[PDB]
Length: 268
Ligand SMILES: CCCCCCCC/C=C\CCCCCCCC(=O)O
Image 1 (cartoon, rainbow, N blue to C red):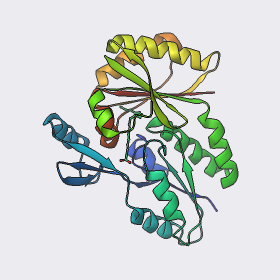
Image 2: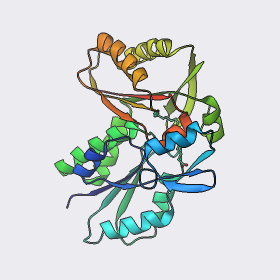
Image 3: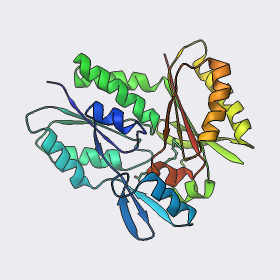
């Protein structure tokens, strides 16, 4: 009776969490100097960083449609519904490909465009896990996640602007972007790591008003010291109880550059 959850490799949730909650991941790939690697299957994050530091060209790719078709038909084998939630259609063709696959299987699959990435997607997955445990219908789940998204704010501080430009995801010093209905918009330029954090503090204070923070996540492109600077400021400003912190997946850092951070705040 419980729906089965599928996602892609861009949520930045821990492997322990994904495995513990039976979340099936369809991974994206990277092409580095003419050779491709499935993220976290054929290449580790340490290995990826070594390629980047060697000035190598990197591109990313959505999963092949056949990977979705195979997964959906197998997971649906006993008649269970599948809910397949993906990073923003404004950032990747993954969602569209999942939808196409859903029209080519006998299984019953509902595909959701999260309009987000990293913990913005991850927190939707975590809420989805809870709704499935509670027995909520798929149609109601879709509506509830739409409401939840209005309470998520995502910022990214770009590590290497030239990488972001090469990757093509811009829809509209340290550049700072946000997602606007799933599309990446650069909204501010900060002069330093420290000043970027002051900007983010003020923007988060504006976003939350007198609301509590339910979850706060920071994903980072191999720069924990920058994350720690943010935690120190945010601990004083907002008295955060716990952060979700992870090294971001190579598919994301391929676009942001090394030294980037992604801040995600879910308000109550
Ligand atoms: C450092 C962690 C940052 C987390 C927030 C990222 C916000 C969006 C900004 C840039 C990342 C873009 C990733 C695009 C992946 C495309 C995959 C594909 O090839 O289809």
